[PDB]
Image: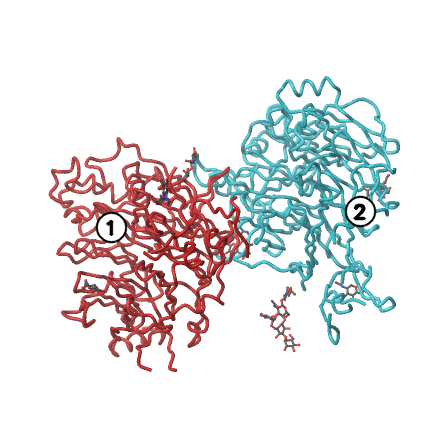
Chain colours: A red, B cyan
Amino acid sequence: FPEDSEPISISHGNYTKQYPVFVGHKPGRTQRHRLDIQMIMIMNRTLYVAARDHIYTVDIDTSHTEEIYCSKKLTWKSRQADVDTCRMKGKHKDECHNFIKVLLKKNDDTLFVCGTNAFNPSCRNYRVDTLETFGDEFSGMARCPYDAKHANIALFADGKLYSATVTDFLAIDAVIYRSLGDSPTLRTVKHDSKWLKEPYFVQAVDYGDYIYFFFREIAVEYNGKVVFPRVAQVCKNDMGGSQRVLEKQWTSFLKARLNCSVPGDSHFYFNILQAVTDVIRINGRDVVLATFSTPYNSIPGSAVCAYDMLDIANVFTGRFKEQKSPDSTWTPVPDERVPKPRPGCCAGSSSLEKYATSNEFPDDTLNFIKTHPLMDEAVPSIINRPWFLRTMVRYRLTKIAVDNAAGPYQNHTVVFLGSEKGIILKFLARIGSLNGSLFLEEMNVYNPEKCSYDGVEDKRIMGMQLDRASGSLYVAFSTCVIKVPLGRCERHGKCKKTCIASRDPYCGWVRESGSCAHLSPRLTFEQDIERGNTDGLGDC
Amino acid sequence: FPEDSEPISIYTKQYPVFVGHKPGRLDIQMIMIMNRTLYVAARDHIYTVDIDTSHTEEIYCSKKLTWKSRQADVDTCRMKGKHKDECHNFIKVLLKKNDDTLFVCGTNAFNPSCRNYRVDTLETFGDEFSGMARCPYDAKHANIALFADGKLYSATVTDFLAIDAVIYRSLGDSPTLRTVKHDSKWLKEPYFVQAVDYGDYIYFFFREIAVEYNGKVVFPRVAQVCKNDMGGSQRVLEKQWTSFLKARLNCSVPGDSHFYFNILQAVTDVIRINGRDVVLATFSTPYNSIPGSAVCAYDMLDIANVFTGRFKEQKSPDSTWTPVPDERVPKPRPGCCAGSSSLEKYATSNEFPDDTLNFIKTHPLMDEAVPSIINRPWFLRTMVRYRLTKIAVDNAAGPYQNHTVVFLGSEKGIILKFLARIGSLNGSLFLEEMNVYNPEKCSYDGVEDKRIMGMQLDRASGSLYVAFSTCVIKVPLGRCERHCKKTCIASRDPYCGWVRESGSCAHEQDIERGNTDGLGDC
Ligand SMILES: *[C@@H]1O[C@H](CO)[C@@H](O[C@@H]2O[C@H](CO)[C@@H](O[C@@H]3O[C@H](CO[C@H]4O[C@H](CO)[C@@H](O)[C@H](O)[C@@H]4O)[C@@H](O)[C@H](O[C@H]4O[C@H](CO)[C@@H](O)[C@H](O)[C@@H]4O)[C@@H]3O)[C@H](O)[C@H]2NC(C)=O)[C@H](O)[C@H]1NC(C)=O
Ligand SMILES: *[C@@H]1O[C@H](CO)[C@@H](O[C@@H]2O[C@H](CO)[C@@H](O)[C@H](O)[C@H]2NC(C)=O)[C@H](O)[C@H]1NC(C)=O
Ligand SMILES: *[C@@H]1O[C@H](CO)[C@@H](O[C@@H]2O[C@H](CO)[C@@H](O)[C@H](O)[C@H]2NC(C)=O)[C@H](O)[C@H]1NC(C)=O
Ligand SMILES: *[C@@H]1O[C@H](CO)[C@@H](O[C@@H]2O[C@H](CO)[C@@H](O)[C@H](O)[C@H]2NC(C)=O)[C@H](O)[C@H]1NC(C)=O
Ligand SMILES: *[C@@H]1O[C@H](CO)[C@@H](O[C@@H]2O[C@H](CO)[C@@H](O)[C@H](O)[C@H]2NC(C)=O)[C@H](O)[C@H]1NC(C)=O
Ligand SMILES: *[C@@H]1O[C@H](CO)[C@@H](O)[C@H](O)[C@H]1NC(C)=O
Ligand SMILES: *[C@@H]1O[C@H](CO)[C@@H](O)[C@H](O)[C@H]1NC(C)=O
């Protein structure tokens, strides 16, 4: 098994503590209450911070102070009647508030916002410019969790809202769901373990004709109790089943195990999926990066694997899985036993042109996909081994941010990894004839002085947002958001050797000033990212 | 998942080393102390060291036994495609018999052979014996060999191609018996670790590919055979074991979901520790997995016990394995020795009825796993690239000889020393971590092979002998002088104590507490 690589550089709290921090204050002048940040996102030039009872915004381009100030504040507190109801059902005072868990750009003028609303999930439209709501409230059931601690997915595609959460207060009825967009609402088959077995929802992406969902669940291929990572497709144009079969349910839902393994005399799999990026074009290919850990009761380890959207689409064209008899191993269904038209193919697809919508699909096709949602094959990662590995630390790798246009010629790919302990890992994607990774830097960004207050010291990174124009990576914790500089250039000061050795696409040696500097689009800008060559230099 | 322990204590170039010189590379395979002699088994040779006369910085050999392969065997070895380095006689078996000879087996250039030698002169005694099934062909392979009541128990491969792994018995004026050839239910690519003699049985410790968990998953196993097994009947298991049964060994961290350590590394001989007969064993995770090692302890009663439970079975092909209902196990019950409790009617296994014989041939595996002593690992190590392998135990350590100290070797020449806590075996206290590889005296042509080949703890000389491929190292059981009264007491090390008559720490103490009440500070 692969040894842990060492980073070229390390940054401790001593240096990082000078990074600007947002803690929810407007500019007008010591009251401190934990923010309960849930997620962050950048739209246009505005950073949105979704939290308890609020969404704060920071205008990125005009924020230069050491304390990052809130620019506009959206306020949405639960009605007292809902708070009281929440408490009577036995929930605690801290959790019976409105935690914002869905925040989406519906269009240029409109935000779609959903909050737990004291275990009575609710959604609203908000004006982008005034952050005031307009129109009727929308039901939140199946669109937004009740409990802020739960993981959930929401995404718009073509006006339709795709969501994944639980429909019920008791958190028993986990669902992948679609609504809005003037199309029928669709859901996964309630209480059906072949469709979903205690899923934990991680990510969805919109690609080609499909929405793909990433998640983990108890694996039926193991009937003692093992969690597998999954990706699933649904057709964007799905209209539900016929009056006889899968009425009001998906007719295109299929899923496959994700393969993130280390090759050996018996493969070792990373099964506990932590995060997945949006689709990123890296080196001609369309790809997602995904972080995995070993089970929490196991010896701790983490990995990043990459997946080509092409390999993902391809797994759904292969054989389906089945149990020929109860309590037997799972085998591939022979294609001769697969109905026509093929389950999981979209109406109007090649050879399905006869079908106006999935409502016209034959019963054999529908009963089949209802009883065979799982594919035989697992999706292979690019390179068939993890791009990055950590095995000798106590923390797990979690969030991911990617810059596929780093450097003078915008042709390096830099990947940032967050962790449950506030450490960020920075690495360079090896490319070409994508060949793994180079560990550039490790850095502790958690700032106890600004982030540890109101009885909270929670170093779990909740989100990371990379922003090129401000040369920053925004790193969210529960109680704060930190503005992290993309490259620690001037660190190396006037030492040319450590500047060149860093192999950091964000940094170069500028002899006109005699110093290591960040890209300034001008003077000479020397770097050697491909090789680390410092022969004839030194030292420090 | 549990975090690692730091030792209470973490220079080792001044230790006496043996490199095979008389006064004025060895490819060591094993060491063992017999009476007052340390035997060093190696390539083409066996070396002896007088334990109680060696005090120089270099340990010298007293007598040397030489047994090189005949040239004809070397040349045949090469012609079969083996390399120059492997085509020698590597000594892999070395046992003291009751008639006072040494029984020695060597790979003999891929043509395993055995011989008796005189203990006094180390000269051959009588004719060579066949080595097939008694000793491996390949020096890199792990093998078991043990005498009990004159019968020789051995585990290895019988064939040049190493396809036919076997647990075998011969000699002792008793039938030769073997495991059923090519029968995966019996053995499935086993890796042999240790055997012990206990009660009416010999117990074999080993690892193999698990039939119950069919992706290739390796499980650790303990198997029994009856010392008095005479083989099957004329029509069932005629020349095979009639008592072979095995069971998974359980070494896991407690919780709702258990994490198992599966790759068995080593097992001690049976050891008495406060009224109980136990073995300690080291395990690691598979080699391409996240690295980790564990020590689990086992009571011989719990091992005896699994063999009385329900057997495992596949009620139908490719199904999950389930326990057989006791209503279905024949009489006599499979695996109980002839002459036993309910088996007085049976003189030898040759009389067992076809029905129980057919059943045991088909059901060598028990449903249940042997639990460890507190149902949890005695010790855990996970933050490191090495794995825990060899084990040596001193169950009568200290002035009052009432302390149990455990030493663990590793594949990287690091040794770990523990006190065994005793509950009202309540775990372990991490006393010390020491690197003892002497690169100066042990390296050879630039290369440093830091794998520990064997450890032998010797109370009488206060030493732990640690064997590497190239040297054996004489390690002080207690590094008392290293530690100042406070430091000394707090070490809680049973071999070390404070003597104010020298104002020093030497071979006053509180081992049960680091009690530094009113002392210090250094
Ligand atoms: C297996 O081995 C372990 C130790 O290696 C034993 O575990 C401890 O057992 C002792 C005996 O009861 C416990 O001692 C108690 O310590 C308390 C202080 O807190 C301890 O435990 C916490 C976590 O629970 C740790 O964070 C902390 O560091 C301490 O270790 C004291 O408050 C207690 O003292 C009080 O009671 C005594 C009489 O009982 C009075 O005389 C005192 O004045 C005082 O009022 C007590 O001494 C200890 O808590 C146990 N746990 C641990 C982890 O230390 C197992 O018992 C042992 N199993 C056996 C013996 O079979
Ligand atoms: C997980 O992905 C790996 C990497 O492709 C697969 O490994 C292959 O497995 C077969 C034997 O099982 C070999 O013949 C190939 O050579 C392996 N590696 C390569 C380089 O492709 C593995 O099988 C996958 N696991 C699952 C469950 O699909
Ligand atoms: C990144 O972009 C630059 C474009 O200038 C590439 O650098 C040049 O690569 C060419 C070959 O295509 C070399 O012959 C030149 O000497 C390079 N110019 C420089 C910077 O000195 C670079 O190869 C690209 N790196 C990638 C794709 O990883
Ligand atoms: C040293 O050698 C002698 C014989 O040469 C071993 O013989 C033991 O003798 C006693 C008394 O006759 C028996 O009860 C034991 O069964 C013999 N060995 C054992 C313990 O099984 C003796 O064991 C050897 N060991 C030492 C250190 O004396
Ligand atoms: C290995 O040993 C452990 C510890 O004895 C066993 O763990 C018990 O398992 C049962 C069923 O899963 C639990 O309900 C108990 O609470 C566990 N601990 C104890 C002792 O109460 C475990 O089952 C063993 N594994 C195997 C395969 O036998
Ligand atoms: C986005 O912001 C920019 C300036 O930050 C502004 O010029 C532009 O009009 C905005 N576009 C919108 C509102 O989508
Ligand atoms: C060891 O012996 C001493 C005195 O003989 C005693 O005080 C101590 O409790 C003993 N330690 C044990 C039994 O573990």
Q: Chain of mark 2?
A: B
Element assignment for label 1: strand
Looking at the image, the residue that sits furthest to the bottom is A30
Q: Which mark is residue B15?
A: none
The one nearer the camera, B182 or B30, is B30
Looking at the image, the residue that sits furthest to the front is A512
The residue beneath circle 2 is: B16
The one nearer the camera, B36 or A41, is A41
Tell me whether marks 2 and 1 sit on the same chain: no
Does A211 appear above or below B520?
above
Can the viewer see residue A88 in this picture?
yes
How many dots with numbers? 2
Element assignment for label 2: loop
State the separation of the CA atoms marked 2 and 1: 69 Å
Mark 2 residue crowding within 10 angstroms, few (<14) / some (14–19) / many (20+): many
Does B48 appear above or below A80?
above
Quadrant containing ligand 2 reads: top left
Can the viewer see residue B304 in this picture?
no
The one nearer the camera, A378 or B80, is B80
Q: Is there a contact, CB below 8 Å, between mark 2 and mark 1?
A: no
Indicate left or right for B484 with A304 as reference.
right
Assess mark 1: CB under 8 A from ligand 6? no
Amino acid type shown at disc 2: Pro
The residue beneath circle 1 is: A206
Q: Position of residue B46 (x, y in %)?
A: 79, 33
The one nearer the camera, A364 or A290, is A290
Indicate left or right for A333 with B449 as reference.
left
